[PDB]
Length: 94
Length: 94
Image (cartoon, rainbow over all chains, first blue to last red; front, side, top):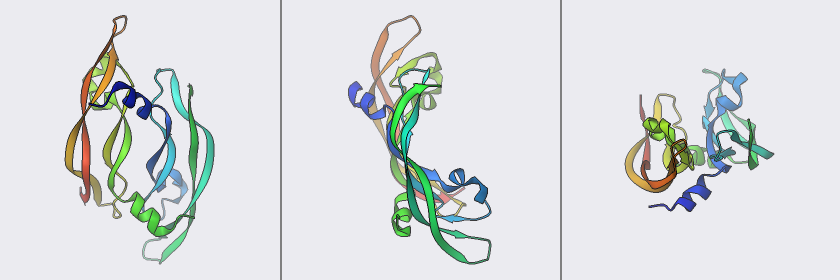
């Protein structure tokens, strides 16, 4: 049984590696098929213990990754794509 | 710049720590306010590279955690709640 305090600290609002789909990140590029289709990014997650508060980023950075993309029967390509990362989170009002 | 292979292995379907909301887990307990409102659980996530295959669990277990719950105007209660964990994932058809 995980003690209340472990669960409390571990789930509290903080940056956590999150597997994000590339389409949600670059939406004006659905006319391509990415591989991998998703990337591991550091994003604010978890909970604030108050309904009024929400977990949001207070410091960000960019990560560049080699992603493959292919237009329907038109050649395999490999390029760089940048994604926004969260280095620090904070519980604040909505 | 993260190399294509690093990104590919890291994002590929596997059990990863995910911060889940307790209501999502116990939709009947909407009557209570849990603290923490969310818990860290091992769940299948990531991607299968072929949108035909989907990342799903092939081995599970239960985790028990001490969670506090309170009814409006009543006292704080502390108890145990069990959540479903994923020990192994696998890419498969829909």
